[PDB]
Image (spheres, grey):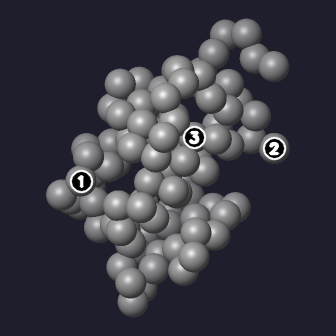
Amino acid sequence: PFEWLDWEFX
Amino acid sequence: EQETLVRPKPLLLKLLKSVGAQKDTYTMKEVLFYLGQYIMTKRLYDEKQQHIVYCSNDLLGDLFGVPSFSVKEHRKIYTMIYRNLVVVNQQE
């Protein structure tokens, strides 16, 4: 669920 | 496409080690990705408002110089990361 720049971490 | 070759300074390098990255030279893309994984694994984002990072009680807060920030603050994020690395002379 953690979105960051170009990526998704859950 | 963020291929800038960089050498993290000691603080940033410590953060990267937390997620298993122990090399000295990276692409910017790698640094950015590993910092995202850092925030994930340290659980520094708000479970109910996931773009909010609360870093006051983490080493990350020393990097950013603030107790909290939003992942929406792209310019600030890039700025603070670049100030914590040295861009390599010989690129490619």
The residue where tag 3 is placed is B31
Indicate left or right for B30 with B14 as reference.
Answer: right
- First in sequence: mark 3 or mark 1? 3
Q: Do badges 1 and 2 share one subunit?
A: yes
Q: Amino acid at mark 2?
A: Glu
Q: Is B14 or B69 nearer to us in this picture? A: B14
| Residue drawn 45% across the image and 64% down it | B40
Q: CA distance from mark 3 to mark 1?
A: 18 Å
Query: What x and y, as percent, mark residue B82?
Result: 51, 35
Circle 2 residue: B1
Of labels 2 and 3, the one closer to you: 3
Three-letter code, disc 3: Val
Q: Position of residue B28 (x, y in %)?
A: 64, 37
B56 left or right, relative to B83: left
Pointer 1 with pointer 2, Cβ within 8 A: no
Numbered disc 3: secondary structure: helix
Amino acid identity at mark 1 = Asp
Which chain is mark 2 on?
A: B
Name the chain under label 3: B
Secondary structure at badge 2 equals loop
**Residue at image mark 1:** B58
Query: Dot 2 surroundings within 10 Å: few (below 14), some, or many (20 or more)?
Result: few
Query: Please, is residue B89 above or below residue B78 in the view?
Result: above
- Quarter-of-image position of residue B3: top right
Whole-Å distance between the Cαs marked 2 and 3? Answer: 13 Å
Q: Residues within 10 Å of mark 3 (few under 14, many from 20)?
A: many
The vertical placement of B1 against A5, above or below, is above
Q: Using a 10 Å C-alpha cutoff, classify the residue at mark 1 as few (fewer than 14 neighbours), some (14 to 19) or many (20 or more).
A: some
